[PDB]
Amino acid sequence: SLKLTALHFYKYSEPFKSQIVTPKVTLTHRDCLFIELIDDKGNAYFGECNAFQTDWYDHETIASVKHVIEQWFEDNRNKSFETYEAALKLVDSLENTPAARATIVMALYQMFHVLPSFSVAYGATASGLSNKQLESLKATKPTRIKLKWTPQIMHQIRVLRELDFHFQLVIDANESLDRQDFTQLQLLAREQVLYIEEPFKDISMLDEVADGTIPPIALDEKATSLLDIINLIELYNVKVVVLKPFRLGGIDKVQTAIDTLKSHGAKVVIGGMYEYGLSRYFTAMLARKGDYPGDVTPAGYYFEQDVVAHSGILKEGRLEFRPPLVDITQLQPYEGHHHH
Image (cartoon, rainbow, N blue to C red; front, top):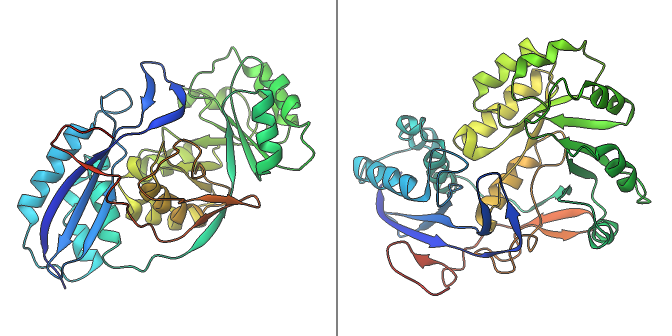
């Protein structure tokens, strides 16, 4: 029954194997804040933060999170806390900063739990369709494949279905559709789509066609807390919820949300976002509790070198996880200037 005793901030940065284009920015490096908490018994526990260099995705940043954790440590260092529950009640006040909260929870979780070894069913996302891409998916043989929405989606579907194995088909629609698209969406109901993520930026568009007509809908970016989820599930015919730990504010909130929505009839999927192998482990850990394969991407898919080596190694259509051990040599500290 322990006190917290030291805090080191670290920073890490790696090339993406391919560049990522987002609306506001192109990504070449995954910049990432790591923390390390040390108890009075001499033990080191690491947390990985999902925040980015700049505020393009979210109001929280690597610099903003570092400040919030810094100040949480000062308010809470050399406090005795007995249980995991007691430890978590010290990050109640961080609820309005879920990325900072999740980073700490990742560390705190490890202080009170043994870390299983396990495998999860591989859910692939397809970036665009090409001939190297398809021969990759022949090799990997995933149980689910995810497609981005394009005007050319129907064609992309048929192109995909030419692989010789069965898989589940998900569409990510990225909040971009309109009464443009009703014809396309209703025709898609015949195409065995497991779910479509976030078709509309405005959720109320959903009762403008009488449900059963289009494929099952999923929440993703609108899954901002367990409240907002249950509200939307009741008000609209949504059957799938995508849960990300950085959005809800930690592992604990995700675990709560899994349990609640297991009874509540909605299917549940767990996901991450350009994670290193520490965060990936915890995400996957939660993902095996979901009804469908998670947005968890294999080791060596984004990054040649990781801070946790081969966290999520793909073998026979499944991703393999052992307890995450941080290569402290790969990390550099926060405050300095470093070659990598």
